[PDB]
Image (cartoon, rainbow over all chains, first blue to last red; front, side, top):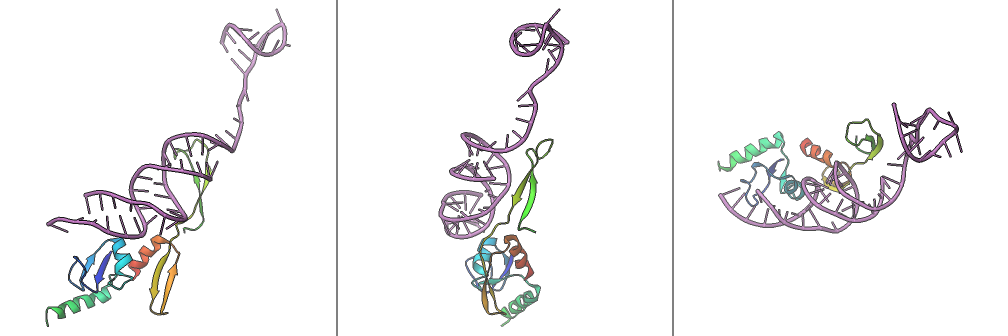
Length: 57
Length: 58
RNA sequence: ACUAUUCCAAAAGUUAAACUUAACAUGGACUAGCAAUUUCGGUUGGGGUGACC
């Protein structure tokens, strides 16, 4: 499923970005360890926000 | 709609022949989650596929 | 249905810019040994055999 990485790990994308990973790798690693989150438009607004203020400052 | 589902079984899946009732039970595995509201780690033995919906329910 | 297998899934790893592993429990078809339901004609100098339909 589509997940939002809290940190940059290996090769997926920039931190905070929304990328679609595998089900096993995603659910058994990213979510329980807090490495990433599911995709909610609510906090996807937070994605766009943090990302906007990233390249800004 | 999973636990204890008892159907019927056929040979060629077209029956002029005998029909024999067959039992079907869901798969059971351990799923560990974390509830921040209750501040408690929870263990669910419930339906696998349902968890895929829960992941989309967040 | 039970006792043992062949594959794909669940669960784990590997490289490049598509591939390999099964400790416990649980599935879909599938191959063997075990088991589950019934059938078991007529004519006929009795019946069976033989013959016949």
